[PDB]
Image (cartoon, coloured by chain):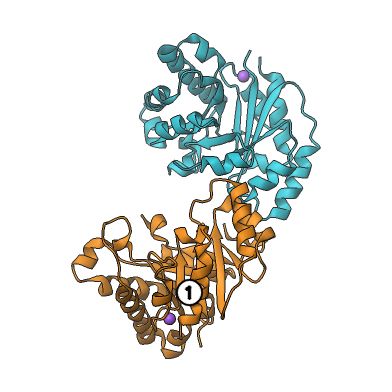
Chain colours: A orange, B cyan
Amino acid sequence: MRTFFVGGNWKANPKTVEEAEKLIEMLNGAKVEGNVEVVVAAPFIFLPTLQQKLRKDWKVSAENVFTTVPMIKSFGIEWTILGHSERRDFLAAKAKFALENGMKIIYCCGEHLSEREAGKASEFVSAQIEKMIPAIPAGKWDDVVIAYEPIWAIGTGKVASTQDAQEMCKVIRDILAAKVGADIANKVRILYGGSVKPNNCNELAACPDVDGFLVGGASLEPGFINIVNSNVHSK
Amino acid sequence: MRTFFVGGNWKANPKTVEEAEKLIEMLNGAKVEGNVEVVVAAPFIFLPTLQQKLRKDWKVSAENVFTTVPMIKSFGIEWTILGHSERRDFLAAKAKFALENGMKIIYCCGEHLSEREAGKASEFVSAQIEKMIPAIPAGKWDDVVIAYEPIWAIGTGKVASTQDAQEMCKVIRDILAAKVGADIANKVRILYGGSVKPNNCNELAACPDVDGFLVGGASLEPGFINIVNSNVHSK
Ligand code: NA
Ligand code: NA
């Protein structure tokens, strides 16, 4: 049922409009296998370039928005990321706002090392999602994707396993089922936003509650297409 | 000696790329009188449009930068604003950085209502400038403009007088003279960044230590050209 979803988040890269154009030419020639929804998020100064030049079967995303949405929409940009850990290091209201204004969102959550070490990851993440849930207007869940970022495994010297991804995506789906029902839970894509590379994307994709990825550094490399194509391993 | 300087800061406006293009067409037809250096700062998503379409005798500025500079430079953008009150509501280091990386900066300062009411405006502003001063590399003062923002008069129900502008720009020039010498003090443009409109720009321009303006809302209106042309009243 759920279409696999892969978002490439360039973060604050590349350093120049010439490199961005070379990256776009590479993406435009990529052969996508299977069935997958691809979105690419880029720095604001590069959005008009992406929007003009990126293959039209993929969509462009902002990496964040402000309390602005009309400017981005005036370029024809439909998506934004919200809540990404770098920004985090309010949100339910900003989700409500972006959605009321016709945006599709990638809503990020995830716990830090102390909560993970304390055995409280599931509690901490559940609470984040329980706060998001009232802020989604009726009829807007089709326009929501949730990304789990294991912030505890980013720059800490700790690594996340494939089972950690699966467990945390299941936690999220279960809290959706508990609070807004099985139909919404069954349709919402829940992404893994930890370190995703060509060497682990296929095993992660196969996890039953992992519907895709919010990709960091590999989104600037030819390996992105391997990650996009890992959808063929997700059932 | 010092060339009058007017920076138009669009802030988070206009709401759409179509309106930005209409504003640029208006600016491109404007007849500038006298001698004046004009810079226009715009949201990041609109910088490539400004850079392509704005009259080449004016320059485009970023409204802020991050600890990025290469991206902006790759479009050929030479300026940025730093320290603007909205952003404020670290900096000396970011000034050093932007300058070392070839940027020209508009460095903002200014005190809040409590300091103004307490009689401490001059002390407060002086301290801000004394912090900026060590962070300017030797030989980079030609690439620095300072803007005084009377933050105490923005959204507080208090208004600033022409004499308040003059007094506060003089304070800044005096601290430059005291700390880095009369030659640098005599050449640095010090701008007034309070409410500047066609009805008060000429009287402000005539103030001896006011070298120009960092314009807010009037920068989106045909009145901007009146403010640019107030340079003929500055001696
Ligand atoms: Na899966
Ligand atoms: Na003057």
| As drawn, B40 above or below A149 | above
Q: Residue B90 placed where, x, y %? A: 38, 36
Element type where label 1 sits in the image: strand
Q: Mark 1 is on which residue type?
A: Val
Q: Disc 1 sits on a residue from what chain?
A: A
| As drawn, B212 above or below B20 | above
Q: How many marks?
A: 1
Quarter holding residue B112: top left
Residue closer to the observer: A39 or A73: A39
Residue pictured at 54% horizontal, 53% vertical: A43
Q: Residue A234 placed where, x, y %? A: 46, 82
Q: Residue B226 placed where, x, y %? A: 73, 31
Please indicate, yes or no, whether residue A30 appears anywhere in the rendered image: yes
> Which corner quadrant of the figure contains ligand 2?
top right
Q: Is residue A96 left or right of residue A152?
A: right
| As drawn, A208 above or below A217 | below
